[PDB]
Each structure stands twice: as C-alpha cells, then as structure tokens.
Image: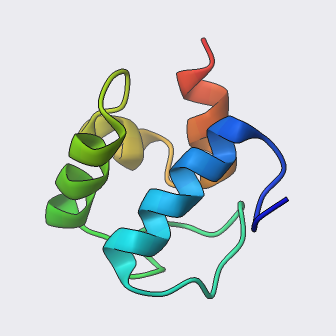
Amino acid sequence: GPGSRTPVELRLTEIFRDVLGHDAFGVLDDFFELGGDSFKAIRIAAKYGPPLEVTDIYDHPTIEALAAHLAR
C-alpha cells in the first residue's frame, strides 16, 4: 500500500513523515536515526491520540515495533 502494508502501520507512517518533514524511510528504520526526538515524539503522540505515548516510541522505535505494541 502507500509506503506500508497494514492500516496501523500506515497511520504511524503518515504521522512520522508529517513530523520529520520527509518520507525517505521504511517500516524497520529507527525514528531517532530518521531525525526524531522527544519533541517530535510528543507531536506524533498528540496527532495519533490513544493508545500511543512518547515513552512507547523510545521502547518501540520503528513502525513495525509500534504496530505490534499498539495492537495488544
């Protein structure tokens, strides 16, 4: 699909490319290596809403890992 393969991963991907200002990445790429930080994590968590939080991104720093986490 549009840069990913499930609706949960697409929802993450969309907000990741909106906050970072670029779309030069895939589902296994570390957020903080793509240019993320605490302030960018706040912006994603606010845009996604529940269940996502800032600390979940530090625990799960990829689209793949966050989709696995949030599905529980």
Write the residue at 55% across / 67% down: 30
Camera-side residue of 51 and 65: 51
Quadrant of the image containing the N terminus: bottom right
Task: Estimate the x, y position of residue 46 in percent, counting from the top left.
Answer: 21, 43
Dividing the picture into quadrants, the one containing residue 68 is top right
Write the residue at 57% across / 26% down: 69
Task: Estimate the x, y position of residue 4 in percent, counting from the top left.
Answer: 78, 58
Q: Residue furthest front?
A: 2
Q: Is the image coloured rainbow, by chain, by secondary structure, or in one colour? A: rainbow
Dividing the picture into quadrants, the one containing residue 6 is top right
Q: Is residue 25 above or below residue 2?
A: below
Q: Residue furthest left?
A: 39
Q: Is residue 39 above or below residue 54?
A: below
- Decide if residue 43 is on the left or right side of residue 31: left
Write the residue at 24% across / 65% down: 40
- Decide if residue 32 is on the left or right side of residue 11: left
- Decide if residue 68 is on the left or right side of residue 66: right
- Decide if residue 14 is on the left or right side of residue 21: right
Q: Is residue 72 above or below residue 58?
A: above
Write the residue at 62% across / 88% down: 24
Q: Is residue 60 above or below residue 19?
A: above
Q: How many marks?
A: 0
Task: Estimate the x, y position of residue 20 in percent, counting from the top left.
Answer: 37, 78
Quadrant of the image containing the C terminus: top right
